[PDB]
Image (cartoon, rainbow over all chains, first blue to last red):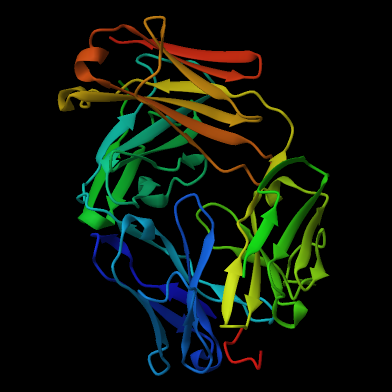
Amino acid sequence: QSVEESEGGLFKPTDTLTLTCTVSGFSLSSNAISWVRQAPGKGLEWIGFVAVTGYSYYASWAKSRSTITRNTGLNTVTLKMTSLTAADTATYFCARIGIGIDFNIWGPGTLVTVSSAKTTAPSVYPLAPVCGDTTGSSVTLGCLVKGYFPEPVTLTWNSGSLSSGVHTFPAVLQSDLYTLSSSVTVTSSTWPSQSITCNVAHPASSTKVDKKIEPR
Amino acid sequence: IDMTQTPSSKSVAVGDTVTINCQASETVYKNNYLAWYQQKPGQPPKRLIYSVSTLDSGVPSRFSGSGSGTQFTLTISGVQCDDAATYYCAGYRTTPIYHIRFGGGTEVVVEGDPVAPTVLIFPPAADQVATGTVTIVCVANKYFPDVTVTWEVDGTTQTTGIENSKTPQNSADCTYNLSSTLTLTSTQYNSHKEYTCKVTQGTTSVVQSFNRG
Amino acid sequence: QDGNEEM
């Protein structure tokens, strides 16, 4: 059994948020589905749920703007929230929350950003070691993903065939733009003999960048 | 209802016992509709305990829950690096209207073996400078406890244009990794020679530099 | 939590 939130993304203030939760492998008609949100770096906030009866109940702060509906035939539960503001920026989860019952399942979440700022594709730069450097038993290379909006980006190395020794750091927000870096560490004899490329994708702008890391 | 979780954060050593308290402003449903969730960054919360004390499937036995009505406790007996996370209580109340309420969370930092960082610095890619700004990257790898990063340009400490990003704790050894960026105009970058990242852990500092050109 | 309990 699983649940999955539909795509969130970037919304302007005063827009309406509409998310779908699609249920698999269990019966929606007899399972209550909640919507829970989490602002970046903050705590979990229950928005409301549709009961096993098909009727919905809401946190008092959410009642005036929020509608939760279920469609048992389509196995969906829909969250509509009107009158968005920056305060509604969050990851939104749907879940069958098991507080006093055995069944509990949570979706992966989807990021909702509410901002007047514009979608911006990232600039991607290689991070190679210092010019001429031959110091160490291993070498760390990097990929700098600068100036994008909204989150997220995806970053792989060698199309995913380089997955060991990777650290992707959390993005930092400044002036409505994000910057992220990722590093990969390999042995001194691996690079630059072997080709190493970072693959960045920014879904919101339908852009991708491939950057092979070359010695300076 | 209100759900008041205490403490909001705690640092604990491997093997210690952690105690987290949750106080509801009214009784939860049937006095035992209270669950505990564990959340690591970028993941949905994972249920550990439900109905006050029932362990979820596969949850280690070092997690136990107790309480009733309005007062509840999560205990982690023998905390491990894999337990570094934020913990939430979650309660259900039917009156006057059905609702679920989460506590504010408890961030648990786990103290593993101390390890000093290794430091790498990355000069800007050659194609950055034409954009009018450059970003220099410093990485502090595999360390515990926390570090501070200082940037120096031609021997003078920088205070502006610096952003830091720290990874979650390693689930095996509790260590962090950190990325620090220094951002300058292209004119500033091309007007100075020595770029230095200094990573300080207590009373040890580890420094890596490079010269432009 | 089913949203139908006799409270």
